[PDB]
Each structure stands twice: as structure tokens, then as C-alpha cells.
Image (spheres, rainbow, N blue to C red):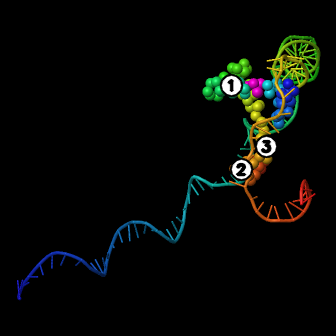
Amino acid sequence: QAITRAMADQARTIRIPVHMVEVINKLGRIQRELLQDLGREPTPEELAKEMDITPEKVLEIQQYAREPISLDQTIGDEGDSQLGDFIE
DNA sequence: AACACTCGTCGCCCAGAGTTCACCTTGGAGCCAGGGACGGTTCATTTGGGGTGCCGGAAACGGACGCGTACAGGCCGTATAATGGGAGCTGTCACGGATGCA
């Protein structure tokens, strides 16, 4: 319990409430189970059927789950300049 | 090759084209005199009309005001036993100097 609560409260650059992290992890887990079972990836409507909630909220959860990237990671094929040198 | 006729060309002579030179009339062009009616002006009405400020009040209307409901985020607890990480890939060289050992 302590480890999972701390993961939810501290693992992400943008804090996500545990009530939303739980649904994100559950969605990912059962979606990978569905992919393994069915042989293809599950579509958002199919995943919403298991979430017992609407595909709009499924998509909102999906776009919420994304994490930021570093402004200083090298973007070029070689190491020449940082991503921060491309942002207006 | 010898012989006896009819036609432009010019001058001249008389009459008017039409033009000038040069004479009488009479409709003037206008100048003024006189008399409207007239249209521009002004001033009396004239009450037909615009006007209005406010309200009884009727009804919309804008909002306050109190009290219900709604997911979002947070806290909390799950009692067989479960008792020391994977993974990292590392071809540089120069080389000054500290540095842990000499």
C-alpha cells in the first residue's frame, strides 16, 4: 500500500491523483490482456465496454496518461543540439 | 499632170447685262408716357395640432438568496506465506597533476 501510494503521488512529473492513476493502470493492463487474447489491439469502443464508461472518457484518460519529454535531449541524428534549441 | 470653184477669219456695227452712280419714300426702332394687376410682402387670426411629465399599475426581468446534488480528490484498510537488482559494456589521445601506495 505504501509503495503504490508513493508511486501514484511521486512517479510522474505532473502529479496525477491516485483515483486517476488506478484507472490508467487498469485500462493499460486490461488493454494489453485484450491485445494478447484477441491477436490485435483493442479499439477505444471495445476498451470502453470493459471500462463500463464512455469512449470519450477512455480517450481523455489515454491523452491524460502521456508524460513529458526532456527539453535537453539531443534531437539530431548526431549529438549537435538540444530540443530546446527548436522551441519558440 | 492641167484646170475652175466654196469655206474661217477677221473686222465692224448695233443692242443689252448688269453694274455702277446716283435720285426719292416709309415703315420704321426705339424713346417716352400712361395704366393696371400682381405677385411679393407683411401682418391680423385659428383653433387643429404637437406635447408632456408623471403615474396607477401591469407585467416582464434581472438578480439575489437559500438550499439541495455531484463527481474529484483524498484517506484508509485489506491477516498462509510470500525476507539481500539486473545490466553494463566498456577500441582516444594528449597529458598535468593529484593521488592512494610506495
Task: Examine the rendered structure and indicate whether residue B12 appears above or below residue A56.
Answer: below
Task: Examine the rendered structure and indicate whether residue A87 appears above or below residue B81.
Answer: below
Q: Say which residue label 1 marks.
A: A33
> Which label sits in the foreground, 3 or 1?
1
In magenta stretch: residue A84: no
In magenta stretch: residue A25: yes
Distance, label 3 to label 2, CA atoms, is: 14 Å
Label 3 or label 1, whichever comes before in sequence order: 1
**Callout 3: residue from which chain?**
A
Specify start and end residues of the magenta stretch as a single range.
A23-27
Rendering coords of residue B57 (x, y %): 90, 11
**Callout 2: residue from which chain?**
A
**Callout 1: residue from which chain?**
A
Picture quadrant of residue B87: top right
Q: Amino acid at mark 3?
A: Ser
Q: Amino acid at mark 2?
A: Gly
Rendering coords of residue B33 (x, y %): 74, 48
Distance, label 1 to label 2, CA atoms, is: 36 Å
